Image 1 (tube, rainbow, N blue to C red):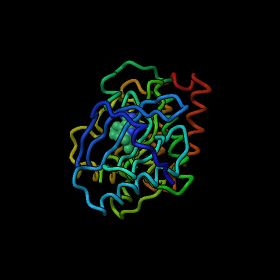
Image 2: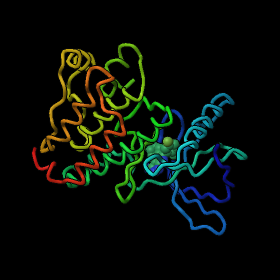
Image 3: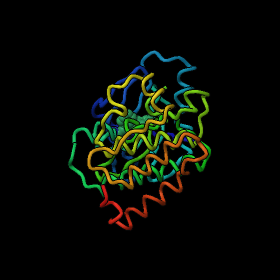
Image 4: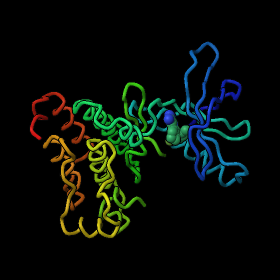
Amino acid sequence: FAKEIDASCIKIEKVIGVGEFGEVCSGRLKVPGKREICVAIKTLKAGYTDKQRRDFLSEASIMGQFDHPNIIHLEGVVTKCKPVMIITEYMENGSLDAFLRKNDGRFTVIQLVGMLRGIGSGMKYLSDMSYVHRDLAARNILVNSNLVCKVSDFIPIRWTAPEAIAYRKFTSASDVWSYGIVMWEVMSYGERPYWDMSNQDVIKAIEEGYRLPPPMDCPIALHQLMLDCWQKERSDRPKFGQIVNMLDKLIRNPNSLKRT
Ligand SMILES: Cc1ccc(F)cc1-c1nc2[nH]nc(N)c2c2c1CCCC2
């Protein structure tokens, strides 16, 4: 379950984002005898019904099940008071996509692989627990000042495995397809998968065996892993545990990254 936070322990600073669901703010959380931390705060949109509130505190419930360094950390919720809130750890560099696009070219290959290794590690934990994300993309990964990447966001054609589009068959294996797309996003500093191709173009390309090329200057071993993730038969794709082990190995033997 999710912890109740006394609203007096919370100080809101600024609105950092908006959406149909409401607003996300940044602020500070100070519990007595504990160090103050920065936090992000998600609030339910004005005039919400009881149904909507329940659907909101349901997302906190789910998040509350996860305790892993690469999954966004739930501080708690406010429910004694109005409006309801969900409080998470503050992630200084925000969303991964936006982040890479503002820093195009600035990191090393090894740093990028580190980010991908963290994301892979969070997805292994998620799928270990029989949870399917369904919406895995760089926009739904958050990034802290130490470049630690954490899975967030508890449909998008370009990111979705063929069997999930065709049969609405969503599993950890279609999450692995999506992870492959994330690797490509990362190594490209946030380029749009499939560029100006339309959704229909993408669907038919995939079906005919088209797969995205290496991003510019991307190691061959990394692109080969993307290709593994995009195997047509879902059973042919690597498991997240194998993805993480492969990335540890590339990291452990940095010469394997030389070939581009
Ligand atoms: C507030 C919130 C609730 C649920 C959830 F899954 C994630 C969050 C959350 N936590 C955050 N920490 N640091 C951020 N920059 C940040 C953001 C969000 C959501 C919108 C994007 C920004």
